[PDB]
Image: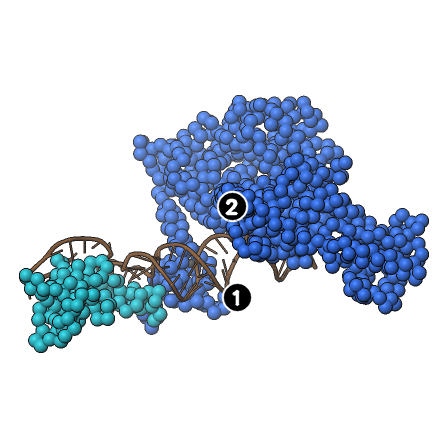
RNA sequence: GUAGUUUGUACAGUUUGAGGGUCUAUGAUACCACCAGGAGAUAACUGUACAGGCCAC
């Protein structure tokens, strides 16, 4: 009996504990690791749980935590040295009030530059720059307040172009893909970063809240200079790289000053509000700052709340700076609690219905959304805890020289580069340069030299997909005979004004030999279906075709642009459609047929795309992939982007075939960005996803006429990965030379 | 191999320097009465690593005659298996045995018992009678 | 609220990597000397726990 009680001590040595009652899902499991949070079944499995590499990293994590948990408390000489270190960080290159004036001069100069071209726009310095919660080499936060009679991507692009033309604010970037689309630049006079945003008045009100707190308390100004210098010394500040924003770090230390007993900043909502309730705190909407001492609030009756304690209590900056890292390494639960400073009380994840596996912070004036959503990967979070550990290990250890401290790179980085989760795919285990789904990085395997025999093989493979599916002229004769017969039948039965016009699979250039007879109806004296009772015509024609002993498969459909009837000719056994003055679908089909009629290579490449998508399990939208219509659209988009544009833009008004298709695969692997640009015809410009706001969707393959739904907005990103794998295979299986059996070339492909 | 085969037992073998003598009961596939003595070296043992022989174990060899006496050119175990070595490579931490190892071990876990005095109070490296 | 096409980290088993005092040669009658308390170091596949990513209902 006691043998098992002694054997379990080795398990208990690293966080294994037996569970009294069965879990709702982990029923048969009996044991649990505190560090792994994964239920365990039996003792031999627990030793098998000991061998887990996840449990191996967790043990080192806990050992580091316990190692620097018990550093000796700082001496008064140590406190004085820490105070000297934080004031020299704050004064030598950290933003002082003099450097705050320098930042204000920078923003005023940039405002002069912008208002020279955009006088209706107005620049507001805000954010981590102005708040006196800054850093030595911060990025300036600037909001643009503009009249609403303009496009926000258009003004952002214009500001980006102005800054690119400007020679002072160098290093202009167009990061329009983050949670806030921001222009980036670098002020040369200060030599520090600057950024441009617009419309984030919630963060402007938060900035005013923080700056009022700063005019109240003095330790405000050095504390986040020190904290943000640690944060940029560990590369946690890059929210684009899965980190946490600098403004969120400002809010983090504001919550610290709120919660560091005895408190040094008062909260915004409290007991002085008679009739206040913690649960309905989101209903207490706040407003701007009055006299830099109060915050306004109003319910749709109003009032103001203090931002000051009536005595600015003075404690040493070194003690504050050490206990900040104490709080945010060993005292405050980073993931369990949302960092919420609207109330002194602890606010959980489900209280704002947010996930529970990383850090969440709330914007004071945007309490609906989590501003700390950029934390995704668990490994990056554990590295962040490790960097907090390295900071607390150094700064609470006495030094030799004489006590002296300096924010060295190597003491906190420990030589290890930061665990940057991939900013493109947001998946751990690989860096930004290691993203497989990155379109632009697919260049690691340049092609072997293209033999002309290989070119002939590719030409034959691309040609066979068309010629095996090309309709013959006798089918055209049969279809026009069925056309005139159906015209005579509908005229003699339903309405003599009915005239027939072949379109679609008979006449779009994409139909096959046994395709459907898609026929448009026209009425004498009627140029549109709006004047016609479409449902009555559809149902009467359906009844009459049912009465026809020569036409079968009759069925009305109302899901098209105008209601249609699908049927089948019994004698030819040929399916077909009847469409009444299609509103747009017919115009789009006519435009596609005109694009086909401009160059038959469009039909050749499209048939090749259809067959190659079929063999790569992505044949049509009936199988969940891109439609053959979408395939034709992206083919036409490639022909546009293959400069000089092989097809033109109708709305704006000599490569070999196998190499044309291989160049389509090459373009849709690496020469084109799906997440950044739009596959659409309407403009010759490389239409960005930021222009059309389809950054939330995977692939922006947009119809030039059907602007309502992006075709790729119906297509998943894992289907995007599948078709990207198909394109890469076309670069490899179809794009590298091979000499298979005659007729088996495409089958081998 | 060479026609001068043989079989027998291991009379003696030094682990440290790596040679010995075998009591051969067979000579070139023909049984002997009485057995004779044939020299063996560690290099004659067709094994990888630091080859060695356990005294008293059975061996099959191909031998030769030299000036110093009979010497076994190539020596293996019965059926071509590897040899053992003089025995006077780590035990299972689950069970204290070379029979299995811990991943292979499926018996329920054992208390931390010292090997020398067979007591669960202490570990064997801190045994008082060691 | 739920399915769909998918990343990591672990998961149990299988197949390969050190066999886990590994390592170390000194060719003709002797070596094995002198312990840690530690549940075993990768690559591949299968099944998978969990969050992240996505499209539709
Ligand atoms: Zn565990
Ligand atoms: Zn990636
Ligand atoms: Zn065992
Ligand atoms: Zn003992």
Q: Secondary structure at mark 1?
A: loop
Q: Nearer the viewer, mark 1 or mark 2?
A: 2
How many residues crowd mark 2 within 10 Å: few (<14), some (14–19), many (20+)? Answer: many
Percent x, y for residue A212?
A: 58, 33
Name the quadrant containing residue A184.
top right
Percent x, y for residue C4?
A: 61, 59
Q: Who's the residue at 83% across and 55% down the image? A: A480
Q: Who's the residue at 45% across and 26% down the image? A: A92
Give the quadrant of the C terminus of chain A. bottom right
Q: Who's the residue at 35% across and 32% down the image? A: A404
The coloring applied to the image is: by chain
Color of chain C here?
brown
Percent x, y for residue A344?
A: 56, 46
Identify which residue, A472 or A293, lies in the foreground: A472
Residue A508, label in figure: none
Question: What chain does mark 2 sit on?
Answer: A
Residue A435, label in figure: 2
Depicted B24 relative to depicted A356: above or below: below
Depicted C20 relative to depicted A364: above or below: below
Which residue is disc 1 drawn over?
A25
Chain in blue, by letter, is: A
Question: Is A319 left or right of A400, judged from the image as shown?
Answer: right
Label 2 near ligand 2 (CB < 8 Å): yes
Question: What chain does mark 1 sit on?
Answer: A
Question: Is A585 left or right of B89, judged from the image as shown?
Answer: right
Chain in cyan, by letter, is: B
Question: Is A672 left or right of A446, judged from the image as shown?
Answer: right
């Amino acid at each position: 009996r006691l043998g098992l009680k002694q054997a379990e001590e080795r398990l208990e040595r690293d966080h294994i504990f037996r569970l009294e009652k069965r879990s709702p899902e982990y029923t048969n499991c009996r044991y649990l690791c505190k560090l792994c949070l994964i239920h365990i079944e039996n003792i031999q499995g627990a030793h098998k749980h000991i061998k887990e590499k996840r449990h191996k990293k967790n043990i080192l994590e806990k050992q580091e935590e316990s190692e620097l948990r018990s550093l000796p408390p700082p001496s008064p000489a140590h406190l004085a040295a820490l105070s000297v270190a934080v004031i020299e960080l704050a004064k030598e290159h950290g933003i002082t009030d003099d450097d705050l004036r320098v930042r204000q001069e920078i923003v005023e100069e940039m405002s002069k530059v912008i208002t020279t071209f955009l006088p209706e726009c107005s620049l507001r310095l805000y954010g981590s720059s102005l708040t006196r919660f800054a850093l030595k080499s911060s990025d300036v936060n600037i909001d643009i307040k503009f009249p609403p009679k303009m496009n926000h991507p258009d003004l952002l692009i214009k500001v980006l172009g102005i800054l690119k033309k400007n020679v002072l604010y160098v290093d202009v970037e167009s990061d329009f893909h983050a949670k806030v689309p921001v222009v980036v630049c670098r002020d040369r006079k200060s030599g520090l970063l600057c950024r441009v945003s617009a419309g984030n008045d919630m963060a402007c009100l938060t900035t005013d809240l923080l700056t009022a707190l700063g005019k109240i308390e003095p330790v405000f100004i050095p504390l986040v200079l020190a904290f943000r210098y640690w944060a940029k010394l560990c590369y946690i500040d890059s929210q684009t790289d899965g980190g946490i924003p600098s403004y969120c770090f400002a809010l983090m230390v504001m919550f610290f000053l709120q919660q560091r007993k005895p408190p040094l900043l008062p909260c915004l909502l409290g007991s002085w509000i008679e009739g206040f309730d913690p649960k309905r705190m989101d209903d207490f909407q706040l407003k701007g700052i009055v006299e830099e001492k109060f915050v306004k609030w109003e319910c749709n009756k109003h009032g103001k709340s203090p931002l000051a304690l009536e005595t600015p209590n003075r404690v040493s900056l070194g003690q504050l700076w050490l206990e900040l890292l104490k709080f945010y390494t060993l005292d405050f639960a980073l993931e369990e609690y949302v960092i919420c400073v609207r109330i002194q009380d602890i606010l959980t994840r489900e209280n704002k219905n947010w996930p529970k596996r990383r850090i969440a912070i709330e914007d004071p004036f945007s309490v609906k959304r989590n501003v700390a959503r950029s934390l995704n990967s668990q490994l990056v979070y554990e590295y962040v805890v490790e960097r907090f550990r390295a900071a607390y290990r150094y700064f609470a250890c006495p030094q030799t020289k004489e006590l002296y401290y300096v924010f060295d790179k190597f003491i906190l980085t420990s030589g290890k580069p930061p665990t940057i989760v991939c900013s493109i795919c947001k998946k751990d285990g690989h860096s930004k340069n290691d993203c497989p789904e990155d379109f632009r990085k697919i260049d690691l395997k340049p092609l072997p030299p293209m033999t002309n025999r290989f070119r002939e093989i590719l030409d034959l493979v691309c040609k066979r997909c068309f010629d095996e599916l090309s309709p013959p002229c006798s089918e055209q004769h049969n279809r026009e005979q069925i056309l005139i017969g159906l015209e005579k039948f509908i005229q003699k039965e339903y309405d003599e004004k009915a005239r027939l016009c072949l379109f679609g699979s008979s006449k779009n250039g994409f139909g096959f030999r046994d395709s459907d007879l898609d026929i448009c109806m026209t009425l004498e004296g009627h140029e549109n279906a709006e004047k016609l009772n479409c449902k009555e015509i559809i149902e009467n024609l359906a009844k009459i075709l049912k009465r026809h002993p020569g036409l079968r498969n009759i069925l009305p459909i109302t899901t098209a642009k105008v209601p249609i009837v699908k049927f089948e000719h019994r004698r030819s056994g040929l399916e077909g459609d009847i469409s009444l003055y299609n509103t747009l679908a017919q115009h789009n089909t006519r435009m596609l047929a005109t694009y086909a009629a401009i160059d038959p290579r469009v039909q050749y490449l499209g048939y090749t795309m259809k067959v190659f998508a079929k063999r790569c399990d992505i044949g049509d939208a009936s199988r969940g992939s891109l439609s053959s219509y979408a395939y034709i659209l992206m083919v036409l988009y490639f022909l546009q982007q293959r400069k000089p544009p092989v097809i033109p833009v109708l709305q704006e008004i000599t490569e070999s075939l196998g190499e044309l298709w291989l160049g389509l695969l090459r373009f849709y692997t690496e020469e084109f960005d799906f997440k950044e640009y739009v596959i659409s015809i309407r403009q010759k410009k490389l239409l960005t996803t930021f222009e059309k706001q389809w950054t939330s969707k995977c692939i922006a393959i947009e119809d030039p006429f059907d602007l309502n739904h992006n075709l790729g907005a119906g297509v998943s990103r894992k289907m995007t990965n599948f078709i990207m794998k198909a394109f890469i295979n076309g670069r490899k299986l179809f794009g590298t030379p091979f000499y298979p059996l005659i007729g088996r070339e495409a089958e081998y492909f | 191999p060479q026609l001068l085969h043989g079989a027998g037992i291991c009379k003696w073998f030094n682990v440290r320097m790596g040679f010995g003598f075998l009591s051969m009961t067979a000579r070139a596939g023909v049984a002997l009465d009485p057995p004779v003595d044939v020299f063996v070296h560690q290099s004659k043992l067709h094994m990888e690593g630091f080859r060695s022989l356990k005294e008293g174990e059975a061996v099959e060899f191909t031998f030769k005659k030299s000036a110093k006496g009979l010497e076994s050119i190539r020596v293996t175990g019965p059926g071509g298996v590897f040899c053992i070595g003089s025995e006077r490579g780590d035990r299972c931490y689950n069970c204290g045995g070379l029979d299995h190892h811990a991943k292979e071990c499926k018996l329920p876990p054992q208390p931390k018992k010292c090997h020398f005095c067979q007591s669960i109070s202490h570990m064997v490296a801190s045994c008082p009678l060691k």
